[PDB]
Amino acid sequence: YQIKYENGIANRGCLYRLKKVMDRAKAGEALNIAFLGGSITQGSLSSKPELCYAYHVYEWWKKTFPQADFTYINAGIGGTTSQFGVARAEADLLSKEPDFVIIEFSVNDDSTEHFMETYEGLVRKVYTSKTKPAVLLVHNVFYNNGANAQLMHGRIARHYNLPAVSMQSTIYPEVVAGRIENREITPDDLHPNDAGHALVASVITYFLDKVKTESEPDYPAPLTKNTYEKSIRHQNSDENVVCHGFVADTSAQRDITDCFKHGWTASKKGDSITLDVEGCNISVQYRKSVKLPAPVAEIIVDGDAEHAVRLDANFDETWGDKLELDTILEHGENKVHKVEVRLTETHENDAVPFYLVSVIGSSEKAH
């Protein structure tokens, strides 16, 4: 095969920040290199941590600027979207004071206006954060059909003048032409193996090298309604929560990939919990278990019990447990909402309790 590396540059964008980082690296400064994304960022399915695309890019910085001290920040969490990204960005990323951030959600997000809005919130939050990091968008692709959410994400890339690179226009073309057979680079048409991770990194490093060897735009008003930029998780530390059967999980989170932490569990029909959640949007995070059977709950907002949403912990897929995030209220009234979650179905032989990870309240941050 032969990749057309120039076709990987989906958006050149404004290179001011990225070139400032390179200049700091050249001067031998200490720099924080970060990655925020789904399972491909976390590193699935590389055979070792050092062979995922993220570590390859990290190794690029080290090798290109041996005088600098780099710190590796991998904030990938498998099977999650930019909607979780904007709510976790402060804790998982921005608290680490990153100098360079890859954002990688284009095969996690669906290609919809909803995800355009959540990704815009994430991009705005990271781009305007204290350390004013260089941001590079990375767009992976599904190898079974060529799909991704780059139509939505790319609109955000062009709106903010951000650099962006794509596998949809580099690797997938060699797959569809039959010069790379899918199983050479991915066992499941989504997660790259070692060979695939090295190809993904090569597309990214092609661009980083071009930038290195080659005044910021005015920060614009949002393109979408941008109602997710402020996204606050309500977890078991929240002082307005009242349990009636649900019990807080106080166990240690070893790291962020241990994602069923800081929430609450329940095993019995009728177990419930009530939360006060401010915003115009409400979403809920909970476990979908491949260990079956498991309980079913309902979530009710502002007593609208006739319109409860069913949260079923019985996962019908097999790759593993999913950290589900369901949007319950969108573009509603911005107020303190009452939220209740109650268990509605249990089984004598339930393998696991229901795990309520968070309720997320969101609203616009004014421009």
Image (cartoon, rainbow, N blue to C red):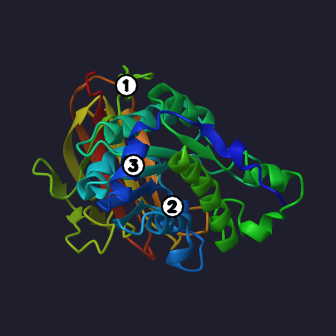
Circle on res. 41: 2
Give the residue displayed 64% in from the left and 60% down from the top: 202
Q: Which quadrant does the C terminus fall into?
A: top left
Task: Report the side of 157 relative to 222 (left or right).
Answer: right
Q: CA distance from mark 2 to mark 1?
A: 30 Å
Circle on res. 331: 1
Classify mark 3: helix, strand or loop.
helix
Kindly give the residue lying farthest to the left in the view shown.
Answer: 239
Circle on res. 365: none
Q: Position of residue 153 (x, y in %)?
A: 54, 36
Task: Report the side of 143 relative to 11 (left or right).
Answer: right
* Picture quadrant of residue 299: top left
Q: Nearer the viewer, residue 262 or 255?
A: 255
Q: Position of residue 175 (x, y in %)?
A: 82, 56
Q: Position of residue 197 (x, y in %)?
A: 62, 66
Mark 3 crowdedness (10 Å alpha carbons): few <14, some 14-19, many ≥20: many
Kindly give the residue lying farthest to the right in the view shown.
Answer: 178
Mark 2 crowdedness (10 Å alpha carbons): few <14, some 14-19, many ≥20: many
**Does 349 sit above or below residue 172?**
below
Which badge, 2 or 3, is on the more N-terminal residue?
Answer: 2
Task: Report the side of 315 relative to 364 (left or right).
Answer: right
Residue contact at pointers 1 and 3, CB within 8 angstroms: no
Circle on res. 84: 3
Give the residue displayed 64% in from the left and 67% down from the top: 198
Give the amino acid type for the residue marked by disc 1 in the picture: His
